[PDB]
Image 1 (cartoon, protein in one colour):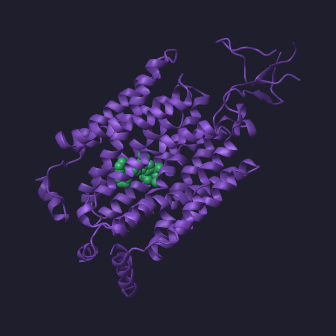
Image 2: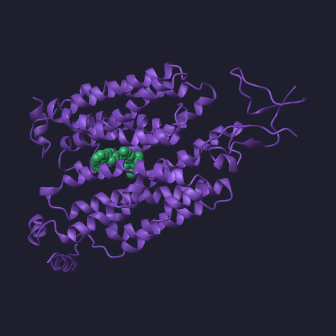
Image 3: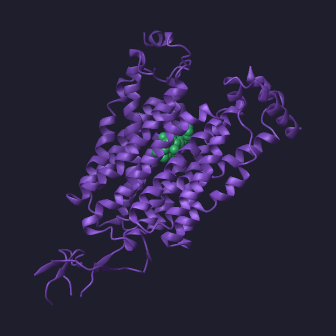
Length: 463
Ligand SMILES: CCCc1nc(C(C)(C)O)c(C(=O)O)n1Cc1ccc(-c2ccccc2-c2nnn[nH]2)cc1
Ligand SMILES: [Cl-]
């Protein structure tokens, strides 16, 4: 087959290495954009501007009411914002405060809409028309759209321009895995799948470095999206996947692509047996994505600085993956997933009840929540591939992944309930994973058996 021909020129070689580094290099900035809203939309302290002010029950001045005389009158005028730590954010620029608390959460929602939208349209287009031709278009779109939001004068312009950047980013991530797996032989088709996560996790460190140097949100937003233009120049000289050319009936160009390598080197829901598994796998993607993005979106509530608390989050992943790796090879994929989920949900519940006065305890069970979900989010993907049959494994993983973003959409929407009850958002934020722990019990497979090529062995393995 094609696998022998790919290894005929030497398999992985000088041509192969130079292609892998270039495509995976922007993945460092890939994770920067997801949590960029955290630093850009930071909310500072503020008090009403007189043309003294009442204080709260804890001894702090109010933020929406002003003394009628030196009755109670709403803050018709603006407010003076702190400049000791945050020179300027979108809250300081546009009045997203008081009666407009929910507006800031809305900006994140449409960002999650853009990434969801880019999975369908671009995925459909990436097969009808050449694969690498989509990658160049996505690279150019994210460079122009990123810099336009840095100069948006009106709030509706900011939301609209951010949505277009979300569509471009989704296609970049999807095409990175598809293009690389085509030119990598099956004998080394798993090493790349582990390097991506390490590069994905290292993105959290880069955001901390740039945030300290550039406090201004207008300059910080520009800096993150600035290098993407540079990657567009290098992306011109790529090589299209040879497997796709033969599939569409374009073999005549396949030989030329192969020759250049040598010189350089030297329907799913149509059967009960699948609908039972799909429903069980459905709640696993949803629950994990719900809790994961519900803890990273806010980190200023705790008593530690935002910069320091971020670097702890980006380094706790390394112990998390090591523990999960040992349990996978010793106890099993299913026992690891269930144990992690029940432990993660319990940790979140205890955080809400515990008072915020003691910061040391508060950050102890807040870091553990991020670390636990990091291990679970890696277990689910590995188990998913082993379960689905080869006929629909490619479609099943994509369908399962395209719904994980649906959980990310709901995550900031539930945060609007803080207006009524401040602790209320934490109640649902940990209740869902615990109820999801009762889904893994009904899964009728485990690990240690040969992979199912056909559906005929699914019932045989059950009995
Ligand atoms: C750390 C974030 C996880 C995540 N976020 C998204 C959003 C931003 C909502 O799109 C998605 C998604 O596209 O569905 N995912 C899935 C994902 C799962 C595992 C991994 C992973 C982690 C460690 C090692 C390997 C992988 C991996 N396996 N397959 N692809 N990546 C990466 C991404
Ligand atoms: Cl993604």
